[PDB]
Amino acid sequence: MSIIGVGIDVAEVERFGAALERTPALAGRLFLESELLLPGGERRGVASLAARFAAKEALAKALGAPAGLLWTDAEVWVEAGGRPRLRVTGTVAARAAELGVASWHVSLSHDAGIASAVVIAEG
Amino acid sequence: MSIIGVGIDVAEVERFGAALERTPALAGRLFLESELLLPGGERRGVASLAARFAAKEALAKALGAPAGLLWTDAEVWVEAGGRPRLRVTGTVAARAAELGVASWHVSLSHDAGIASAVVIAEG
Amino acid sequence: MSIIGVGIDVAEVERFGAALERTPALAGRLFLESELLLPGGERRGVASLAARFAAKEALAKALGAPAGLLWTDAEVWVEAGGRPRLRVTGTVAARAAELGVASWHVSLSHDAGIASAVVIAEG
Ligand SMILES: CC(=O)SCCNC(=O)CCNC(=O)[C@H](O)C(C)(C)COP(=O)(O)OP(=O)(O)OC[C@H]1O[C@@H](n2cnc3c(N)ncnc32)[C@H](O)[C@@H]1OP(=O)(O)O
Ligand SMILES: CC(=O)SCCNC(=O)CCNC(=O)[C@H](O)C(C)(C)COP(=O)(O)OP(=O)(O)OC[C@H]1O[C@@H](n2cnc3c(N)ncnc32)[C@H](O)[C@@H]1OP(=O)(O)O
Ligand SMILES: CC(=O)SCCNC(=O)CCNC(=O)[C@H](O)C(C)(C)COP(=O)(O)OP(=O)(O)OC[C@H]1O[C@@H](n2cnc3c(N)ncnc32)[C@H](O)[C@@H]1OP(=O)(O)O
Ligand SMILES: [Mg+2]
Ligand SMILES: [Mg+2]
Ligand SMILES: [Mg+2]
């Protein structure tokens, strides 16, 4: 395997929350139902959501951000141990296959009113 | 070798310095004596320290942040050329062995009142 | 191939623009003519330029930031699809050869008055 792409993204939490409040349908456009919930069942907060948005932008970047990709075809899930993970389906999986991506790595940080993600695509 | 994990962490310098001043024992809990000094012998400043804290969080993230890890079992050292490096011992080395990590890569930045680190674990 | 280095850099856009305005010769010292233009032909703006500066710092970091490297020996170019790319020549290529670097990966983000880059060197 070799590195096929890297992405980084930094989002302002306040701006992102304002985007969500302005267009009620937006959250469901960007996120699967599972992503909108905490492991317990509570609704996920805006900073954690901004970090997942940053993950999806970073993932897009690592794939060369082509047209035709759906936000709901990338999913951030969470291991029992707490590690965030990427699962790709449909349009995003198809693009990753064009490029030969076998493995995804993500990390998130959110603090200081800002959410950051890095994504590495390997294959 | 393949990538086994990635971590990113962004820390607010002011907040971190306030944490250090509030609990005198904290610095010695987070850092080895060597990390608290500049190559000359002067005491390392708060921004540079916040960046090493971010490195250790990022390293934890790349390992899936399990319980039982000691801050003093990760060490940021510095090459003659100035490159920051990671050395892992004890509990952190043990966890990296569980995952098959052979090689560590780190970079630091601190500026704008914020410290950032990225860590990649390969093996 | 394995990872040979990683770099991250975060630059304040305002500070960087002030540096450019203060010393007219600075832009031409840091950037090739091609980097100072948008694909159309318009002059590239300060935030996008700060992000390319961050890329070159990040690239320097991934190489262990030795003496003797020229800013104009690293070039950020842009694919038809929009992906940013690194090309290295002269002094920067020579240093990458010392270390065995075969492949470069970069991503950029600029938002919230700040520009960020990550660079990975593989070989
Ligand atoms: C995986 C998924 O969920 S995809 C689902 C559908 N969503 C998408 O495809 C969204 C893709 N995102 C976009 O189109 C974005 O506008 C991007 C990636 C082009 C830019 O990201 P933003 O968050 O808007 O801005 P940000 O400042 O973080 O990034 C800009 C940088 O991205 C980089 N970029 C631009 N196009 C691309 C591309 N095709 N591939 C990779 N990087 C790119 C550039 O370096 C740019 O800076 P520059 O113009 O100064 O060189
Ligand atoms: C190497 C050493 O020095 S270890 C020594 C002992 N120290 C440690 O083990 C510290 C480990 N650190 C922690 O427990 C931290 O609270 C962390 C890593 C869980 C989070 O980091 P913080 O700096 O507190 O917050 P930050 O916002 O930067 O990171 C949060 C993100 O980390 C990610 N995260 C949470 N748990 C884990 C995990 N087990 N592994 C990897 N990433 C994780 C999540 O994506 C989370 O955001 P989300 O809840 O919105 O998904
Ligand atoms: C590819 C090219 O275009 S090279 C062309 C010519 N330009 C250069 O060579 C510029 C090289 N840049 C420098 O000298 C910079 O001052 C650097 C890389 C040392 C630091 O970057 P800056 O943007 O000034 O500050 P920033 O806070 O982002 O980075 C500082 C961190 O860089 C790291 N660093 C220092 N020296 C090195 C090195 N030789 N290699 C890698 N990382 C280093 C350290 O972790 C440092 O933080 P610390 O002192 O708290 O440990
Ligand atoms: Mg952004
Ligand atoms: Mg943090
Ligand atoms: Mg900087």
Image (tube, coloured by chain):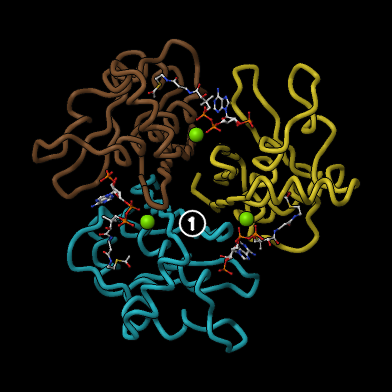
Chain colours: A yellow, B brown, C cyan
Residue A29 locus on image (x, y percent): 85, 47
Q: Nearer the viewer, residue A94 or B59?
A: B59
Residue at the spot 32% in from the left edge and 41% down from the top edge? B47
Query: Residue flagged by tag 1: what amino acid is it?
Result: Ser
B117 shown above or below C71: above
Residue A47 in sight:
yes
Q: Chain of mark 1?
A: C
Q: Residues within 10 Å of mark 1 (few under 14, many from 20)?
A: many
| Badge 1 element | strand
In the displayed orientation, state which residue is furthest to the left: B40
Residue B117 locus on image (x, y percent): 41, 41
Location of mark 1 (residue): C116
Residue at the spot 37% in from the left edge and 52% down from the top edge? C123
Occupied quadrant, residue C93: bottom left
In the displayed orientation, state which residue is furthest to the top: B68
In the displayed orientation, state which residue is furthest to the right: A25
C6 shown above or below C77: above
